[PDB]
Image (cartoon, coloured by chain):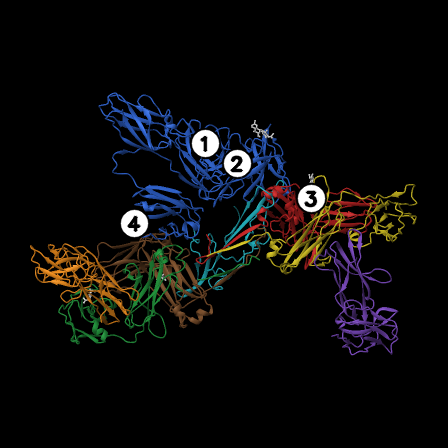
Chain colours: A yellow, B red, C brown, D green, E cyan, F blue, G orange, H purple
Amino acid sequence: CHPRLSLHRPALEDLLLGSEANLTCTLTGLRDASGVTFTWTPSSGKSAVQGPPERDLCGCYSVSSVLPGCAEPWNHGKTFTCTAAYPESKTPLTATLSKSGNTFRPEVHLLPPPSEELALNELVTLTCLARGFSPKDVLVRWLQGSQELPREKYLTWASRQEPSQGTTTFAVTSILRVAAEDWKKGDTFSCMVGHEALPLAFTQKTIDRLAGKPTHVNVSVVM
Amino acid sequence: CHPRLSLHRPALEDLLLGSEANLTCTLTGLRDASGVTFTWTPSSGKSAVQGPPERDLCGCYSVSSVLPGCAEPWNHGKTFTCTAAYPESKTPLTATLSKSGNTFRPEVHLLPPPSEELALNELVTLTCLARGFSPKDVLVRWLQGSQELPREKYLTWASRQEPSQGTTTFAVTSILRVAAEDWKKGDTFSCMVGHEALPLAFTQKTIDRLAGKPTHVNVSVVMAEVDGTCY
Amino acid sequence: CHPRLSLHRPALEDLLLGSEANLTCTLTGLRDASGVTFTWTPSSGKSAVQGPPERDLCGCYSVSSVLPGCAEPWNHGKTFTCTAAYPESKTPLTATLSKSGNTFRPEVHLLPPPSEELALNELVTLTCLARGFSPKDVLVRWLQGSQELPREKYLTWASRQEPSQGTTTFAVTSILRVAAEDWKKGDTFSCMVGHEALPLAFTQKTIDRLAGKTHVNVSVVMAEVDGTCY
Amino acid sequence: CHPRLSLHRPALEDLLLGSEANLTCTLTGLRDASGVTFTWTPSSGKSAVQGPPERDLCGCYSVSSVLPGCAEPWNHGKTFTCTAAYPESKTPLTATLSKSGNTFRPEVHLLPPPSEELALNELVTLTCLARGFSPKDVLVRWLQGSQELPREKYLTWASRQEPSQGTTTFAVTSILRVAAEDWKKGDTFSCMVGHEALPLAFTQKTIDRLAGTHVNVSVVMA
Amino acid sequence: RIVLVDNKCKCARITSRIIRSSEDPNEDIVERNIRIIVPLNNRENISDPTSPLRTRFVYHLSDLCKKCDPTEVELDNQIVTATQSNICDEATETCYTYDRNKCYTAVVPLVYGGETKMVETALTPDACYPD
Amino acid sequence: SPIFGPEEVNSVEGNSVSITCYYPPTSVNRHTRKYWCRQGARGGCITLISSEGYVSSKYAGRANLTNFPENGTFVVNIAQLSQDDSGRYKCGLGINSRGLSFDVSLEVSQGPGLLNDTKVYTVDLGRTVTINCPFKTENAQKRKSLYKQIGLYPVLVIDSSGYVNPNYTGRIRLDIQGTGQLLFSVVINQLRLSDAGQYLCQAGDDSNSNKKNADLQVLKPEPELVYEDLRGSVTFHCALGPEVANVAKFLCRQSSGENCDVVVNTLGKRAPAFEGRILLNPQDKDGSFSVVITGLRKEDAGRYLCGAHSDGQLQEGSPIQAWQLFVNEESTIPRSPTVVKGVAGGSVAVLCPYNRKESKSIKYWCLWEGAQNGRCPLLVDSEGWVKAQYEGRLSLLEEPGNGTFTVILNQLTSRDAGFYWCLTNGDTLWRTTVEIKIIEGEPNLKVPGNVTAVLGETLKVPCHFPCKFSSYEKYWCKWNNTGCQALPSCDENSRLVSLTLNLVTRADEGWYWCGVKQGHFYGETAAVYVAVEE
Amino acid sequence: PMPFISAKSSPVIPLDGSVKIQCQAIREAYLTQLMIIKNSTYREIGRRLKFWNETDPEFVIDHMDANKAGRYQCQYRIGHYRFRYSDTLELVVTGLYGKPFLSADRGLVLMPGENISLTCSSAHIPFDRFSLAKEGELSLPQHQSGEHPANFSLGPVDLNVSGIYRCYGWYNRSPYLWSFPSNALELVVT
Amino acid sequence: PMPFISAKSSPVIPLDGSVKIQCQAIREAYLTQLMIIKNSTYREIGRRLKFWNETDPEFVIDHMDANKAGRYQCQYRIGHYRFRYSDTLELVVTGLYGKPFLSADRGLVLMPGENISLTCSSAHIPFDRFSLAKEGELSLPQHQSGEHPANFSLGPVDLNVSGIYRCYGWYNRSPYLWSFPSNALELVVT
Ligand SMILES: *[C@@H]1O[C@H](CO)[C@@H](O[C@@H]2O[C@H](CO)[C@@H](O)[C@H](O)[C@H]2NC(C)=O)[C@H](O)[C@H]1NC(C)=O
Ligand SMILES: *[C@@H]1O[C@H](CO)[C@@H](O[C@@H]2O[C@H](CO)[C@@H](O)[C@H](O)[C@H]2NC(C)=O)[C@H](O)[C@H]1NC(C)=O
Ligand SMILES: *[C@@H]1O[C@H](CO)[C@@H](O)[C@H](O)[C@H]1NC(C)=O
Ligand SMILES: *[C@@H]1O[C@H](CO)[C@@H](O)[C@H](O)[C@H]1NC(C)=O
């Protein structure tokens, strides 16, 4: 149908866990031959080969270009503009590529389980809240003790923008439900949140039973 | 693209606050024209809202119709049979939906502000976690004392199904930020969660600095050898 | 001898357990025969029966009259007057009464068997004491667990007026002999005391092999103390 | 009326506490014959005396004869035979009485007050139960410390036959309500049961506070 | 001292108070007092024959503070009735002390004449008077 | 806690005393044993008399405890008091060791006697007193003076030459009446609390010196105990003497610092807290007016000193009348809503509660009005009288009929807000105050405006409602002076509940309503007028 | 042989007085009566009913009168039939006749090795006999004369013999009825 | 200069065995990977996501075989793109060829000042090289020879030389494939 051009960015998972940081500058909708020509303003000499020539929904041909030989070594903040071409009218299609600043480091809090779920002595729901990061990109992983739990061992909502004054910020939450016996034994659970703004690309918060030291419970018995 | 018909359950916000149980039946992928017709089995509201032939991406044509209704038929388990007879089809198609069964009630949890957030004394987060409710939909509203806050002061996430611990259940979060002075003063903040499965179709949980983690507790145990009534 | 007439109140067993309690008026000191006529203040279905005469002390005709269906009026407080007219008389005898006022509630008590009876380990004596009620009418029963003990396995005394430390009050005591093996096994023994003034016309006190103690120890947990009470 | 002769044993109170114990032979139903002869075959010891007539059942000239000084022969175990006559028939009226054997000592138990009475800070009830004595007779009395209490300050029930299967035994109960101040002061309260089967003839049992409690409580607080 | 709960049937009184300080506004004091009256003369169940005494008393702070009574809340233009807790399922709770203001009877068999009667007694006599 | 009685009782030796202690009339309390103990040095009540037939040996024959359930109180009449009875007794209910008592400090003092050389004089605070003192006949025209023996030395307070002490300025007068009188009177007006003590007379400095010692004591008022419930009402029948029938009456409220905090004066003053819930009825011939204070709360319990002064503030020399209010807080009064938001042009329906014993009485709905000392006129009564201004737009239905009645008020405007009261003819009167706040918004029930019909013409008038109201029953209730009644019989769908009038006659013209009810409880309503023309 | 009986007050007693008399506790005795001696007959005057093992029974008599004065004996009751008695004491009435006159031939400061005699006599009283009582004695005095010039010799006096001495008249027909105390003599021995 | 990589088990792991490897944890690393060097490239076999402060990254390998044997190294991710490497370790497999023969010319009880030489060789195996491995060593042996009569000289032995010794064959074409253990000798030094 209607041709269009879109430039994406590597998912934060690849950036923070691997070397598959392959940008993409693709086109949706194509009803002509393979008269495609891609140019990237950087001239680092890496490989910018065309990806898999396939189609998209509604009988549309989509051509995708990736960067396999480049892991995005653009820490200096390069523009990285991509321009496409077609045998259509004399008006080449170019993409917009820029690095948004005003990055805000996430603030991550780990909330102890609700007391009502502690009483029933079946399970406890540890919640992780990541609030106050400007880019809407973050990934939350969980650990029980020292072993990272599988991706089916918790739940995570999207990243939504939170009401504020002037500045724009997002937030996300996750819940890990663990058997009450594990919590009462003393096993230490942990929430890792990965965001770009952090210098170390991951923030850790640890929670375990008997986390409240300053409490001063007093027990007295009369006759 | 492809002519497909679908039905949507009534919006909860218009079902709990009030009784307007207005449905929605959407047909997407009109072949060439907008010559569509609609029909509900309970043809009481003969003036059904025939939505305009709106456009969509990739040359897609959609005609979404809204049937005005009330909570009475919906909560009583009525059957809806929205159809469509677009010319490109030699046989009309039908869609069906109704109130969902096997619904578990949410376990609302209002959690006080975290320990380290109160030290900054700038803003405190109050989290209202529903959990365990089987239907996807839920309403979260927030109150400061007795006056409900406007929906622009708190952030509420969607209802994403939680990992299967036997049966399928959902859970939603909703943070509300408060001036630390309001918390340390002693005001009470309430979270109202409205879900279909609940008895009254509404529940609330109220927390203030007194109903949170206390820094000191003095527990005294008294024995009553004579008689247990404890006047 | 000199003729006498008196109205006898219904037995407390029929009052607290029986739906209908009759009220009787008894006469004595007849001369030669019994041609008496009995009349009462109410007449709502008073199908009273004269009945046969009897023999009094040293020989004398004596007949008594019973009015059934005197339960609801008794609760209400109606005045019951029995009037007797024998042929050898000119002014019929009268006797009036009504439900007693100024009632009090018994203070039932159970007492564990004395330690000196557990040593012999053959039979233990349980005591029930219903004390401090104005109308002398009281009922005492015993139970083993939830099953009633036979009426011949316990001794219950008569209701006596205790010394006046206020209004006149009445006391009753009862004892029960129960097996030492049964006492130590873990069975519980109850005493049920019935009265007019009692709230539901009955009450009960239960005792077991631990009651009255010793060195019994108990545990309390208090699971979560810093637990967002709401 | 109907003539009737009977003989009643001496009371336990005067026998054990009083100086001289009577022995009443009663004849009723005569309604006449004021010159009724009362004589005893054991014509020894003291001299039997007569008694004035009284009204019995409104038509009987009840006549009673009493023999002071019967404590010593009663303790010895003599058999007494009362004799009388009436002008109706040609036969006299004879009755016999003697002290019965098979006597079992009481098992005196002084129970403590219930715990539901000390809260009200009113009179607290001390119960005394005597069990397992054969003869129906028994004395029950109370002492607060070392002094007896007048018989109007306490209540003693009658002696009743305790339903049993082995042998015939009688039990009696008493209650004394002492001011909660007296009970909590530490004073000692005792019940004396007097009987003839007892070699000492009187067994006393005492109770007070601090007789015969300690509870241990475990706390967890997670 | 703002009272948080007075659970009569379990007999726990939880009160709370705030003690402030005009210096270093981080050492604020929140004091909560829980007073518990533990009977030593009450059966496990409220019945005559049952576990001659109760030796184990468990007090979960999440069940003392439950409020199973709906309230009214005005959201935008309307009032709506709303519950206030999850764990108040229909009652079956087993609490220890007696309720001073509520009846507690029992039923006992007995023999009268030529019949048997299931009499109703009064385990708390003061509070049971038909008025 | 809930037990209330005289916090301190006074009496004299050998004089009977009566202590009334109030408790909630709950069925448990009325049948619970009532005791009257006397805490000592052992930290335990030693019950001295109980309602279970127990009278101590010491209190035997000189005391009796009588419990009235209907009032909800019990009285402890104690005769032949003695100084040894001075102590802190405790009222209460049930077991002594619990905390259902009310400490009562009863104190007694020995009376005078054998003292013929000293006079006595007791009068109510702020009243007028007079003392007559003679002088010897030998003194024809000689100095007469009054001496005040204050501590170590005496001082002159008044002389025969016109000297007046600064402490007795303008309120002390010496009188020498004619008719050949040789006796002088000292009259003091507006007695204070600083004049108690011994005075002496003197007639010159000569040898005669006809002195006579006298004593002056001032008696404070005795608080008349009032035991009311939370959110109930209290009434103060201030009936001061006629001599102050033209003075400015005030109703103080004592505090910790012994400082007045006037609740309601007679000079158009009123504390902000008590706004819109306190009346001040006009005084009668003798000065007997009633001050009604409704909407009782936790902090509305204290000592009320209703009296008179020129300016209306408590000051020395003012006759007063004390009180003592106790708010139960174990109230049986339903906690009905205290604030009602109405939508201009819409309506309300306020459920006013009463006591179920007076279901046969007649009810009143009163628009509170300030702008004065306080007032509260009726608007609608149950017998069938409706104010002239509120015609067609007010009704008072006895539909709940189980301790509550509805008041329906539609066509709300901006002038219809404010406090309102509900009244009945019964003895157990709660004046529940409900405030109507007016909020701008679209009424739920659409009115359609007021219509006119031609003579003998069928008229159809529908009113629209939301389908949130579809569950509720729908009615019209043509309005009448005695009370509107639902018309006999009407909505095809979720909206448009209609009324049809087959014929139009002069009797049909008037006001009609359309509204909803939840079986027996009423709700929003709207009103229309039907006129007839030819 | 027999359990003793003692009086806790001085035997000398004026009209309207009171005295406490103590018996000896017997372990098996379930009753302890204080009896009377009159014409060889017994009349109950006191009764303590208790098994005495910790403290001796006491009997208090008030409103002392002529009839009450006499011989007192304590009678127990062992078992159902056994009777037992105790010693017998005497209590007398004083103050119904004129007070006799007492005098000392010495200076009342007699040395511990000297001899002092007390002379008691009256001129307007026919007193048959005289009795010399000493203060502090808990039993009847052992000094009594028969002649009108009643002479009482003390012989080798000692520290214990020191005390207050008085004289009382005595009639043969009325052993338990004495006269008013005489002039007390403070016989101090040093 | 680089983090150390230790093996919790002996580097001579038999076929179908197991081994645990611990790398020197650095707190500033949020991801640690185990890389096996093969054909001059990396290959991830174990990943640990955590900020280690108390323990260290412990990886487990089970069913030791030729494919899994070779050079191992821990690669740490520091920051967004920084990489910190460590020292290398070697893992070998034993049990692919026959057991050689090892002997000593002394009595195995040589004094601390004596010299002992160990001869390892095979007759029916073309083994190119031989390696002398001491039992209990956590690092690969440093004693190896190239000729058929593999000679191992110890010189001035001491107490530290005491232990159990064995010999393993070594093919130049199979760097990390070792043969079955040879006869064990206890070279106790006292
Ligand atoms: C539910 O959907 C129906 C669709 O018709 C809505 O009904 C319309 O509401 C508007 C609101 O002003 C009216 O103007 C229209 O006349 C209504 N339609 C009809 C056919 O009457 C209804 O409002 C929706 N409910 C909610 C709560 O938004
Ligand atoms: C309703 O119709 C009546 C017809 O008489 C109009 O009359 C007035 O109604 C108001 C009610 O708000 C009364 O206060 C006036 O007293 C009425 N007028 C007279 C002369 O009595 C009324 O205006 C109509 N309502 C409207 C137009 O809203
Ligand atoms: C009352 O009398 C009737 C008639 O004799 C009898 O049937 C009934 O059992 C009696 N009820 C009593 C005595 O309670
Ligand atoms: C006989 O009986 C009377 C009266 O019961 C009693 O006073 C008396 O002591 C008894 N004994 C003698 C010997 O009179």
Q: Do labels 1 and 4 share a chain?
A: yes
For the residue marked with disc 4, what is the amino acid? Gly
Residue C138, by quadrant, is: bottom left
Q: Do labels 1 and 3 share a chain?
A: no
Residue B183, by quadrant, is: top right
Q: Tell me, yes or no, if residue B99 can be seen here.
A: no
Task: Give B152 or F396, whichever is nearer the viewer.
Answer: B152
User: Counting residues from the N terminus, which is met first, the one under dot 1 or under dot 4?
Assistant: 4
Distance from label 2 to label 1 (Cα)?
27 Å
For the residue marked with disc 3, what is the amino acid? Pro
Residue holding disc 2: F395
Tag nearer the camera, 3 or 4: 4
Residue holding disc 3: B68
The numbered dot on residue H159 is none
For the residue marked with disc 1, what is the amino acid? Leu
The chain ID associated with circle 4 is: F
